[PDB]
Image (cartoon, rainbow over all chains, first blue to last red; front, side, top):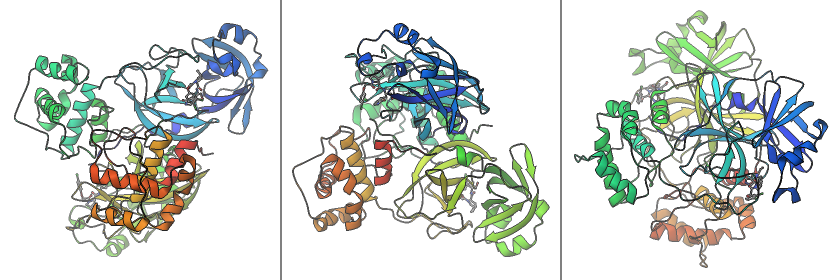
Length: 306
Length: 306
Ligand SMILES: *[C@H](O)[C@H](C[C@@H]1CCNC1=O)NC(=O)[C@@H]1[C@H]2CCC[C@H]2CN1C(=O)COc1ccc(Cl)c(Cl)c1
Ligand SMILES: *[C@H](O)[C@H](C[C@@H]1CCNC1=O)NC(=O)[C@@H]1[C@H]2CCC[C@H]2CN1C(=O)COc1ccc(Cl)c(Cl)c1
């Protein structure tokens, strides 16, 4: 038993992490087969960072301008191209540690592991959710750009996130691995801001099921509610609407615990209207919304990855 | 910016994880050079698990009884010996992925990363603290024994924990890598229990400094307090006494933020006496005590590992 914010083992990604330096900018790149992926703003310098034109900036670059460092081995760049907001640096060497992988784009509400890197070297790993407003509450300092977010699905790494920037509230924005930003953000210094977030309702319910599985039961009740009546409460407390599909996805957890999904909604309602009254749930005094139903099933049943 | 419960990159440990099967028991082993380390209770079966005599049980074993599986390669056991509560299985092959390592024993209050494994395959990674009562609040299911806890110090893995068991409150107990239990626990089914815990005071203060570094300032005050007067409050709220050495260790964080350690203590006092009044600190509605001063400095300055 126990329930922890658990990241995927990072080894497969660690072997793909490289250093990319161009001009005065050093960031991280992702080396898969003979391509290194990195944020395109590496080709910028200070004055370039207000209103850049990256097509103009890229045509002025040379392969030899890109210093790519895989540990203590320099990788010769032999081609480069821009794909949206990522740069694809073709290098003369395929990464022998390339795992099976996919580039996937995730939905707000879904979670992933971030391997925070500096200078191509992994610093730490942690779990994140894509917020409804397409930001992530990460932990990122200067030089962390190009760190990736990912899931692992048996032996296959699904890369979903590459880090580009921090917003004024201290949250983080980036792209999928095809270079397309999550949310309405651009890789420029503008006055852009996150915009209002909501709590991921289905995830909160998943975490309540994790709590029941782990022996926290105090918030349970005999009450029930309709899906419509629950969503009128969710709206007031700035929770995402719960769909019938969310109810279906919570089925297995409902079955294991014997608590109907709509019954757990009634519990959530009471927690929203009354608070926790000094109690905790799974060591939290807040309703936690960064575990998906899958995350709960994964942890509470012991799925591994080969 | 941002602050996350961050684990170390797990790759170096992942390459050491193997499966050990003996009889009806399958657990994880740690393969370093030509030795596999695993919990000695692998040599037990159901009836063996009440009041065992492991010296008796081990002399009845044969090298060939130990099925050691490194991925899809079976490792031939050529010797075995007991060291306290761990078994050392000598195998005919040195692990080519053996990192530089040390066996270290940690102090309550210190943190480490756990690579949760099943069947020798990594499932997830998360950060833990050694509680003052020598338990850890982990996430462990049947088959997770032999998973290790560790820190990474540049390129060197300091293994500090191997998992053996869960206690009736859902917390976890285990040994250092020399087989010596953390705390007054034994690898038997007895009525043993954790025993009363305390909150790791120096860590809470570290996390308050992390909050200030990250722009959470609402809990700060002009007040100060003496170390003695703070500790009279700490005792009432079941917090560990703060020592002058703790104050010294918090020096660098005090210097970076400009908040005297004893001033931050005064803030903690007020949080203890008054609660948080609906506010959060670093996304928590609880005072968090599983970040050490080192963890905070590490994350808020970007230390990596090569
Ligand atoms: C890339 O390493 C870096 C990552 C940032 C730095 C601080 N936290 C992060 O996650 N990205 C940036 O510096 C990007 C840069 C590329 C696109 C736009 C431009 C500006 N920017 C920002 O992240 C701006 O916010 C910001 C906040 C705090 C700090 Cl210290 C900095 Cl350097 C930037
Ligand atoms: C080893 O894989 C296993 C890990 C346990 C299992 C559940 N959570 C864990 O962390 N260890 C044990 O099963 C040990 C075993 C070796 C020493 C004593 C004996 C009993 N025990 C326990 O952990 C007893 O507690 C316990 C609680 C809940 C469950 Cl499902 C189980 Cl199997 C054991």
